[PDB]
Length: 224
Image (cartoon, rainbow, N blue to C red; front, side, top):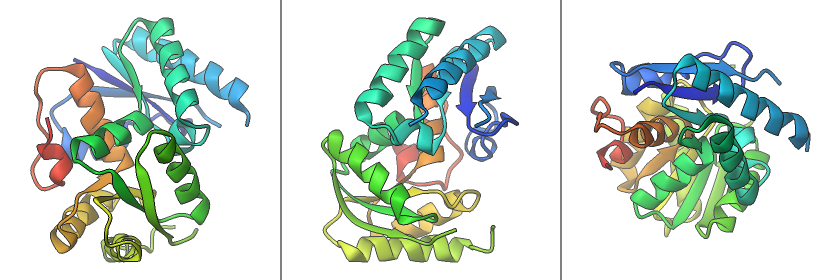
């Protein structure tokens, strides 16, 4: 069943992880362009309707600011609005992350972002609203001169800030995320959830059938 994704850039490309994780599945995407919540809700609902018209069986909102920054209740209400607009099962990358952390038994979660501290602050408020425990946070600041090596280093530093954590949430970074995740899990013995990959994992479960991801991309993809 075709999975539709709402994406931040105007180009509306399927995020690059889908071809790595699920190369045999049909994905389409629609791009929004760019507390301006009024315009956000309306474009989200509009683009969900578009993906429905294009033949999506499920729709996921796939962007970071969009799914997390306005809180858990907002995330939940916008999901309902999309479902009412469209008549399809709808979800968001924030939900996918929550579903992923929960599947992996991660209550106490360290946060790692390539970007700035504010990314971690906002994800952490969302997660606490949903009754997870944010623990240590590290960021890099903001270009793709960051290698897998430094994505791995970042997560390890976030974790060492609170070695009692159950798992790690990695956000931003980007292309090299799916390479870092298994190294980090190997070195720490703790799972790592990353936003975009969790979005794909979650949207694939929502759609049904039991498609599995290609191997080598982390403990999450072993979760049904």
